[PDB]
Image (tube, coloured by chain):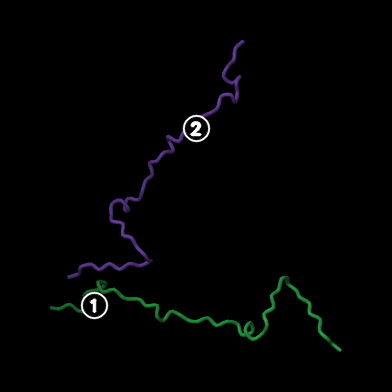
Chain colours: A purple, B green
Amino acid sequence: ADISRAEVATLIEEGYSHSLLAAAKQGSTVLSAFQNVNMGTKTTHLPVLAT
Amino acid sequence: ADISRAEVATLIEEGYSHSLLAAAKQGSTVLSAFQNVNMGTKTTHLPVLAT
């Protein structure tokens, strides 16, 4: 005797959201804690004080 | 009581030169000795006098 939800099947569309997928990515700790030195080739030499 | 070269370490950088990194390439001898025939297909027939 009445129109229910599930008697209109498809005229009603399911929605989507990314609010639980959203940006909270864990970067490296050592990349934030310490200086990032740009390297141009596989090996870099660093002089350090010794005496 | 003094600074030797080995006491300065990698504050001394080593150098690079490409003055020795070149050679002329040598072509095929048969491609300069003989006629280069431009081929459009895998096989070319050439009839020759035989008797």
For this orientation, the residue located farthest to the top is A1
- Mark 2 — on which chain does it sit? A
Q: Which mark is residue B6?
A: 1
Q: Which mark is residue A16?
A: 2
Q: Position of residue B20 (x, y in %)?
A: 41, 81
Q: Position of residue B22 (x, y in %)?
A: 45, 80
Helix, strand or loop at mark 2: loop
Q: CA distance from mark 2 to mark 1?
A: 67 Å
Name the residue type under label 1: Ala
- Mark 1 — on which chain does it sit? B
Q: Is residue A15 left or right of residue A28?
A: right
Pointer 1 local density, CA inside 10 Å: few below 14, some 14–19, many at least 20: few
For this orientation, the residue located farthest to the left is B1
Q: Position of residue B19 (x, y in %)?
A: 39, 80
- The image shows residue B2, relative to residue A36, as above or below, that is below
Q: What residue lies at 57% left-to-right and 19% top-to-bottom?
A: A5
Quadrant in which the C terminus of chain B is drawn: bottom right
